[PDB]
């Protein structure tokens, strides 16, 4: 039974400090050199989503002030959501979503070769379903700052708000590696989140605001740079926006479109605290948005896919990305396998292992533990650094 | 006589909206592709400074709550400072500070050739003393969103907090072009800022927090990447930090160093509201910081200069930057001069003028007006776009 | 029983001519375009070592003048050592020591695939233990000038002095391929060198001077460019040198350090002619150097490894080198295997075989003979030519 007083637990593994720790982290900074594969970086996207996220949190924070702990002003609710929004894409690897797919699929292959036999079937699932949410969770709680001792040591509320997939790999979506399970359990516990299935907990309500803030921004801003990429026509974009509201003339429309969409998202979160604060709500917040808002998002996205996502230049770049990644995976994971169980790696792999020196995985460590170390490294790379190293390799 | 109720005027040319308009602007986004010249971009620097800025504003906001308008919570004071911090470096051209110097000095040369004769001596001063603060002011109030009609249309308070040099070119520091004078006058008026000299007003008090937030971050973070650039030794850095407090072991120190420096900055702003809220205070906030804090900043900076700024690789890159800029200035300003007064530009310059098409300066416009248009264009370029165009030119 | 009159046999497979033939050879010239893998070429290293080598030979030549054939002035003894020093590294492949390791290890792999089955187990050992000394020996006696008929046709003394590993592959160190055995036997015979084990002879005494001249130069000069590479600190280097003696201030120290080390090496060779001229001496000359000299070498080397050899940029370049080599080996050795025993090579390999045209291995030749031809070719390549061809391949 979700309680607004437990769901906003300020204890850590206040909200303003969560924000700063994320902004100063090397993982966040690297987003400035990480982009989605195009035919506007992951960092500028994260910043925009955090504005809309904060705004969403503040609106609902005002609307439901009496239901929230007396210590929590709306500006505090906005901060928790803003922070989660900044951390949201911190785990994706070079080449973004495409790189995510490239890694997941590279694993289904390496597996069909036994590279993963030394692993149980469950641990193996962690890689076969590689999702950036799981990697981001590990980065936030294990890799940054206090390594393997709380990590970024954020508030339980920010973490709960970050976890859109609070469950194990057991659509390919999950946000917790077999190695973070104890952490997810403790967090869920502190937030008083029901454990529906065994290794699956219920979502923290605020995750819905973060998600909504994310699709609101992809929806509108993808159109904007889809325009500066000459892949979209002004009239169509202007029409889609005017559709809900009633190049700088567009930024002004964009501004109004964002207001309405934020209002619509906020006035859907408030309308559904019953099915929200208890049990589960049917899918995502956008579906429960009123007609013209719910459609502006759908249509905007559909447009991006057709004219941007489907472009063949993008396709060809995604192939290059895939190849750059496999070259990397083959090398590091190959080295992980070569030294597993105390085996003496052959020359060439020793040097690949030296590249990490202090970050290298211990030879006597189980395969899952060491592969995680390889993925930590690769997933943390900036796009250019990845291509660079694949090349000079 | 500065009044905390007028100094926080929420009318515009609320603070949360100032923040978002800055984050969504093309000018801000471009900072992600703008760096200082090295031997960590201007965007990540801006983000960090804004965290420290917000924090400073919130601390003093709490400390002086009763002196502030009853509508202004500390979180509102932090937001005004955070916003000004985000806009602070929005006007610098490609190659950052080096590009700033390259442009200013390119003008002292072009002037010694008469390219500026068609201009009065005052208007000419605008370029001879080119400062990014003046360009940023024009970008915030004239170029973005509502072009030449309020621009970003920010709050008077954010603008007052942005203006660290609220005066005309009449150290080479000023933040108002001859063309923005009416705007500065109106702003100063709305904030009730004394007009000491004729074309020189008094600083808004919060500017001091923004400045302090800026040197606090350059001071500590320049050391950090000075380290990942192998130009600095861990022991020296650790020693300097331990000097005030008593690679991840450093981020933790960095964290503590920031707290102390923020505390020190806040507990200096409060100590001096008399010489602050009335007349002028001796220089900048750091000088009025207690012993170990005031020295940690000084020593950290001194260290960066010697080992980073002085590096000869940087020097050589600064030469390349200079050349890239002159190639650009020669082209666009050359074209500005060729068509001045209705003169028919010779071929080649017509094409350079075509590059702006809609942004091109009107042939019958005074030279100062058209040169401003050329600088708007060049200064807004990302580093790579500048080099790119100089090349393909 | 070693005899100073037989050990300096001037007959050939006088010392001044050995010197010139080496300097004019294409193999030696190519050292100017061959470097060790860095994070100063093999040619400048060879030149420096030859100065110290000559000097060593002249000092001991004076000290033991009455024990040497009455025709041999010290300047003649220096020349034999200087010549051997110039030839010393003439056999290493592109990427130097790293390339040496890359080839040896590429073979242990290709072997674990049967590419070497057509070869006996002994002949196979020649490649599994690939050492530049063996390749250099083949180049000096088989490849240059009078191909397969004496080669460079040097003096027996220079050759004996060149051979630091006068034995078969039967640390991975040996300097004679199965194909050069008859030559080593004849040489050893002419110099009257004991045949301890069956396919292993005793070292010519002067080899010790060559070796000492080599580590003396790596020891000091690696520090010098370790300095111009900013991987070392002046104080530490200056301290290490001052340690035995008691940027131009360093070249002067370097000069003194070299004198002392040469003196120390010379006054260790003379002290041990008994265990030298008969049977074997415990290891290498440096170990038998007095305290401060013996330690200056050890410490200087240890320093280079830690701060230069261990640098991760070097590691990554070594990976690139490995890959460039395997691409080459796979191609040429692959072609060697395809046509073995008169098999018709498939297209693509025919073209690879055409690249050598006249140097191509005869299809009816045993595999060891043809693989040797492939290694001759690859090992003789300059670093850039190797990378070039791997690329355009």
Image: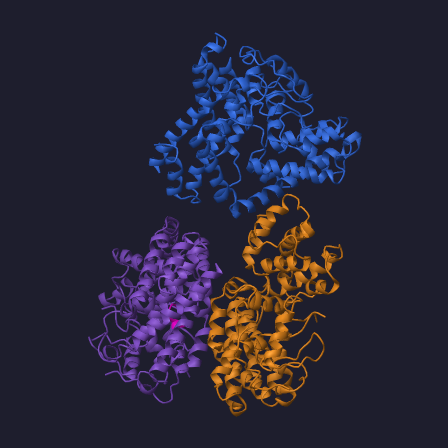
Chain colours: A orange, B purple, C blue
In the image, A191 versus C76, the foreground residue is: A191
Direction bottom: furthest residue: A66
Magenta-colored stretch includes residue C248: no
Q: How many marks?
A: 0
The stretch of residues the image draws in magenta is B85-89
Q: Is residue B2 above or below residue C46?
A: below
The answer to if B86 sits in the magenta stretch is yes
Residue at image coords 79%, 33%: C344
Quarter of the rendering occupied by the N terminus of chain A:
bottom right
Of C256 and C34, nearer the camera is C256
* Magenta stretch, main secondary structure class: helix
Residue A383 screen position, x and y as percent: 56, 59
Give residue A81's position: percent from left, percent from top. 53, 78
In the rendered image, the vertical position of residue A112 relative to residue C24, given as above or below: below
Q: Is residue A157 above or below residue C178?
A: below
Could you tell me if residue B347 is visible in this image? no
- The location of residue B322, given as percent across then percent down, is 36, 54
């Amino acid at each position: 039974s979700l309680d607004w007083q437990t769901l906003l637990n300020r204890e850590r593994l206040p909200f303003h400090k969560d924000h700063d720790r994320i902004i100063f982290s090397g993982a966040f900074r690297r987003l400035g050199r990480k982009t989605q594969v195009h035919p506007h970086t992951r960092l500028t996207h994260s910043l925009e989503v955090s504005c809309v996220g904060r705004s969403l949190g503040m609106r609902v924070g005002e609307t439901l002030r009496a239901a929230l702990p007396d210590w929590c002003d709306p500006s505090d609710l906005g901060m928790v959501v803003q922070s989660a929004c900044l951390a949201h894409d911190i785990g994706n690897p070079p080449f973004g979503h495409s790189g995510e797919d490239a890694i997941r699929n590279w694993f289904n292959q390496a597996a069909g070769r036994g590279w993963l036999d030394a692993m149980s079937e469950t641990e193996r699932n962690d890689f076969l379903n590689f999702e950036g949410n799981a990697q981001g969770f590990r980065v936030l709680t294990q890799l940054e700052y206090h390594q393997f001792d709380g990590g970024t040591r954020l508030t339980y509320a920010t973490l709960g708000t970050y976890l859109k997939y609070p469950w194990t790999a057991r659509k390919h979506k999950f946000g917790c590696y077999q190695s973070e399970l104890p952490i997810l359990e403790q967090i869920a516990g502190k937030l008083g989140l029901p454990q529906l299935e065994e290794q699956r907990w219920a979502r923290h309500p605020l995750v819905y605001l973060m998600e909504a803030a994310d699709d609101i921004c992809y929806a509108l801003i993808d159109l904007e740079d889809g325009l500066e990429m000459d892949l979209l026509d002004y009239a169509e974009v202007e029409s889609l926006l005017l559709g809900l509201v009633g190049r700088r003339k567009l930024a002004i429309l964009r501004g109004k479109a964002i207001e309405h969409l934020t209002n619509a998202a906020a006035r859907a979160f408030v309308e559904q605290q019953d099915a929200l604060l208890a049990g589960t709500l049917p899918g995502d917040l956008v579906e429960h948005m009123h007609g013209p808002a719910k459609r502006c998002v759908l249509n905007a996205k559909d447009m991006a896919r057709k004219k941007i996502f489907q472009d063949k230049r993008k396709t060809l770049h995604e192939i290059g990305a895939y190849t750059t990644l496999e070259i990397l995976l083959n090398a590091f994971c190959g080295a992980a396998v070569e030294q597993f169980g105390g085996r003496t790696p052959s020359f060439k792999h020793r040097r690949i292992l030296d590249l990490l020196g202090n970050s290298a995985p211990d030879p006597k460590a189980p395969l899952h533990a060491s592969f995680l170390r390889m993925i930590d490294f690769i997933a943390g790379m900036t796009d250019s650094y990845a291509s660079e190293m694949a090349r000079e390799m």
